[PDB]
Image: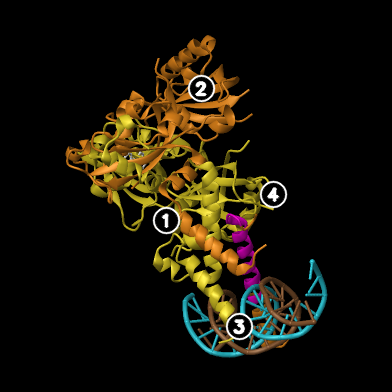
Chain colours: A yellow, B orange, C brown, D cyan
Amino acid sequence: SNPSKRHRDRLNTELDRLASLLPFPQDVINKLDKLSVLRLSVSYLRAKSFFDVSLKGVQDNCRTKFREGLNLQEGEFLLQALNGFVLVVTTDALVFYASSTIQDYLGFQQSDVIHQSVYELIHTEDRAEFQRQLHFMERCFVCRLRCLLDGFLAMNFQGRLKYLHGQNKKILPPQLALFAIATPLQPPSILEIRTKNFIFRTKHKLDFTPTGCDAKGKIVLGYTEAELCMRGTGYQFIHAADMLYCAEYHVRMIKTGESGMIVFRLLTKDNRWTWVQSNARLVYKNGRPDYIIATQRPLTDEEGKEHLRKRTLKLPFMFATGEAVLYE
Amino acid sequence: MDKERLARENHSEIERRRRNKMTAYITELSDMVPTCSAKPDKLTILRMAVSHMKSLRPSFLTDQELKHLILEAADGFLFIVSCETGRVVYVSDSVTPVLNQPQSEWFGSTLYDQVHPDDVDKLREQLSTSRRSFICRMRCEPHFVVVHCTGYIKAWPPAGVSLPDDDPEAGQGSKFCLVAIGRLQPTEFISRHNIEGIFTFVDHRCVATVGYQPQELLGKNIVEFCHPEDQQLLRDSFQQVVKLKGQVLSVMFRFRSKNQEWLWMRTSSFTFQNPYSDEIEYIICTNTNV
DNA sequence: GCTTGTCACGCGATGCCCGAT
DNA sequence: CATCGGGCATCGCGTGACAAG
Ligand SMILES: O=C1C[C@H](c2ccccc2)Oc2ccc3ccccc3c21
């Protein structure tokens, strides 16, 4: 024995007793280091002190035991419905709290991000922006955060600035912390996953009214066969930036029986635009045109916009972008 | 410089920063526990923190604390409905500060009964057969609110929750359920209408011209946004542009902007004819600020 | 085969407590 | 009522073993 080791052993005993009380699974506690043990102890104390002043059930008229069990998980239900994660950030850019679902979206463990500088999770070029959002109260912005999943993920932050009580700063008044929900982003376009050789054929009347469709077509466009023939001609499906090109190539097909390769956008059943490279042929009957057979291959947004940049003809509305709907 | 020496100094600095972090966390603990801040050494601070945490105490937060954080962040109310019939299986108390409705009005109800009829069809599309995100109009003469819903499809019944035999849920037998949160919430642009005036295509520049998002215009008639003294003139222009196919017709009228202001707009209109049957597919309009 | 980090240990410089002046 | 030296307790520093990555 010797005094220094005895004091160190007394300190380590206290540290391990602190670790055994942290509200984490023991497989998480066992692989913690002393520094993060103290860090998350401080985090737990600060959270409890805030909830002691800020915080505090189905109607007794609407009380059933199944509803009570659902109410006791209402928090986790909201968290799972978030489609993202919770983030509470102090004025010092410290992560006051982060929900577990952050691991599902960024790959970071909750126990490693709590009480740490939030800038470590945010892209450098965006950090300044976040700081300007940390200092009316309602906030709505966008930031790219580090993503370890399988390098960065842009995320919409929707939140508010509220006073973080019970922090015992030195006695300082409470500072404005950001309570926010972080969600992913949205594009309005359908790119195939198994893009390669997903060629689908569609049958049309002479006015390009759909009459038949194969399975891959029903998968790409999202309509059933009956739904595809109840919305008028195919021009109701075509992006307004492509209608004149499609009309020109329809004239070409009427004149010579073949239309040629044309790149244009079709409206899904989700009211999204999907790029297709198509070729419309005319089938005949007793020497007179009978119906159209169009064989299309879905394209990515990249190839689609490249084709639009290399457009044959210059036509009005060529670079127009917008949303559409379709009725019967 | 000497590699071994700079490795040594970097390591010493790292250890010193670790020690400083440890003592800073000790000071935070002294600030956080009861009578420490009413001064002691490290061991007493640690023992008092151990006792305080023993008093306070798996999840870092309780379910109510997590709910409090989410609601403080972005409001909203949770509802769990069945995808079969829309039957409201659960609704939180937050429906009262959100929709000005008691929990009873939603319990024993269905989701279609609580939103606008024009949206019922849409809700079916969102309830047939993971993540879901939509916008509807919920009730509170009746008054409706635009409500944004974000949720997911979950297999029913949920794990951990006990379903007794005498419970109303015992006989429903729903397989899937939507668990969601509902929350309250000089240029030109082109557009395509049917011959009656319904917005079927809206340019994205609408936002910069009339202040509306494309979804706020699609499905609505353009005359709904036009001043009453110009409504019949606009309707006559739409009537005559159909009779004179290919011809361009311009009409000036007042448009109700997003701020419910009146913006003078010039609309050029012509028809798109099917290159085989010469029938009118839609009306192309270019709407310009004046 | 290198890098960053965790943990223990040796080691003095003060700290606290307390008989003994 | 202090002040003063004992011996053990706190505490900060630097270094070495060891390991995840
Ligand atoms: O090939 C298509 C697809 C499409 C369609 C497919 C499925 C469902 C709805 C609409 O209509 C068209 C209309 C005009 C065209 C002109 C030239 C080449 C192809 C076309 C096509």
**Pointers 3 and 2 in contact (CB under 8 A)?**
no
Give above or below for A99 relative to B166. Answer: below
Q: Give a yes or no on whether discs 4 and 1 share a subunit.
A: no
Residue that carries the numbered disc 1 in the rendered image: B59
User: Which of the pair B165/A143 is nearer the observer?
Assistant: B165
Callout 2: chain: B
**Quadrant assignment, res C14:** bottom right
> Relative to A224, does residue B201 appear above or below in the rendering?
above
Report the Cα–Cα distance between label 4 and label 1: 31 Å
User: Do badges 1 and 3 share one subunit?
Assistant: no
Name the chain letter of the residue that bears numbered label 3.
A
CA gap between label 2 and label 4 equals 73 Å
| Percent position of residue B42, x then y | 62, 68
Q: Which residue is mark 3?
A: A3
The residue range painted magenta reads: B15-35
Neighbor class of circle 4 (other Cα within 10 Å; few <14, some 14-19, many 20+) is few
Tell me if I can see residue B187 in this picture: yes
Residue placed under numbered mark 2 in the picture:
B248
- Disc 4 + disc 1, Cβ < 8 Å: no
Pick whichever, B201 or B276, lies toward us.
B201
- Residue A171 badge: 4
Position of residue B124 in the picture relative to residue B66 (left or right): left
Q: Amino acid at mark 2?
A: Val
